[PDB]
Amino acid sequence: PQSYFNAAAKRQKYAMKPGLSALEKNAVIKAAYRQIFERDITKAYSQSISYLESQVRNGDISMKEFVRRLAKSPLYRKQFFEPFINSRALELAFRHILGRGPSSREEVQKYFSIVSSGGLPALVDALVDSQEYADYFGEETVPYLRGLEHHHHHH
Image (tube, rainbow, N blue to C red):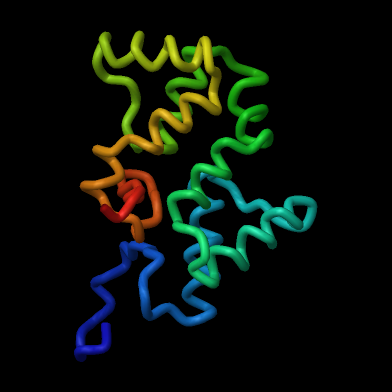
């Protein structure tokens, strides 16, 4: 708070927006990994991570694609499906992408059909590319728990 004020703002929201320094962008990227994989991946987890890092640092790719790549990666595809089933992967995906679990029966069975046929990656595309969560929430906002998803398209 650069307006002469105590540290009341402890809940910070990361967003890929014009006006971010190197340290800021580093935290934004790392926070994304910490949210989707809900743990601190490092060392063994790199290379592709480092490559995605520089891409989003430049602002070359949208923060939305960064997220959809991670969730559609074999890592998430395995860790959240190998010791689970379609219905459980459904819950896990919803909780990570939308921040809300399947609430409505229609909702459950609707996306359950997607995760059963097209699979988890298809469920990812279905949830992430949702124009509702895209258009209304903004493309800059990092998807933290109870946060916002990113805007796809511009117009």
